[PDB]
Image (cartoon, rainbow, N blue to C red; front, side, top):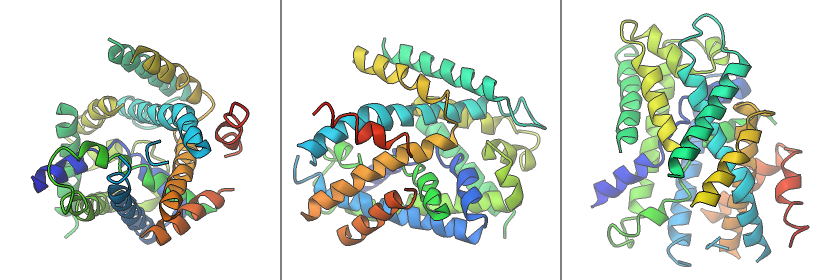
Length: 328
């Protein structure tokens, strides 16, 4: 009942963004303490957002909001779904060819063609539970193995930190068929998302006790370097499981259109230039969704407008704010 809903919520939240985010979130904070503080802030922000969506999605059942709705429909077809589809494939590419280049980083040409090949493969397969189980093993191993050896620039940290919390806005869509949403859906979020937040904090401190702060910047795949410095004899299980589960997390005309325009997103943009490109448009419409409810919400709105006006990206406002307004 309740534990099943909690497990389902945890499963759709812990994605392939916990071992890709720290490298980009430490390059902006340049510290360890502020990094964990930003991670906890992102966790509590995702918790509040999911708790608000649990009360906004079960009362109006695009469905939450004319022109704004059209913009959301237009943005979710170019810069939201295809961009997030390319980030998952870029994360899989930078992790399956990382052990091959031990001493030095992999070439940019190799990771792009390998990511493009991964895009065309799953787009063809989809046009015709094992991933979740293997994904939780790495998160459990890194946390457990981390404890046996233990005892402007502020807006980009939120963008990279909130990418790990991907799926907090679609929780009420797959949780209204379990039990009564009276005191079960808001209860499974107020203790389910913070449980992932504490899980992410316990996973981030496992990196700082093995490798120092300066080694995290020059490491594209932070999990493959943690797998050889702790589990030296068995070091191939980390880059294999996180890659076998990443490819799983990633309608014939809809899949083809989502795989064609996603290939042109990895050519001029790296894995870091796309997280701040997707989280910009995503949180822009998230703030409009919270603002639509008002017209927790007093804080969700004041923190969402700051996450958008602080970086102001130039190649994004002419696609979501100019592309459809000429069509409408």
